[PDB]
Image (cartoon, rainbow over all chains, first blue to last red; front, side, top):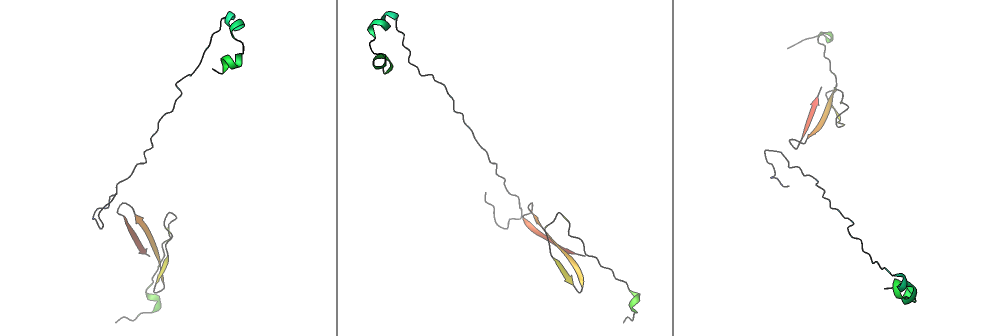
Amino acid sequence: NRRDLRDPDRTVIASELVEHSFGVTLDKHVYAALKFTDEQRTLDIRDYTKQVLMP
Amino acid sequence: AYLWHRTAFILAYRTPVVPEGAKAGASFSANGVALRWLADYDYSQLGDRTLLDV
């Protein structure tokens, strides 16, 4: 703040140090779910790593 | 004109003690008398104040 020099009154204006805040949160659950009927697991799938895990 | 014996007039001086809660001021002399000098700011009036007493 600024005040006139040699002003007969001597009051000064205070300043408040106001701190603000904001929140960060976890809100999503990203997933990939695969169900294999036992027939598909036994016969169709021939290389689990290359054919299921990588996709 | 006044003619006086030395034991006619008694004069006593004492220097005030600088209080514990004050800015460390100096001590001055006036014709052999010791004078207490005190200084203190005035934030409300934004000005310094000084006193010199005995």
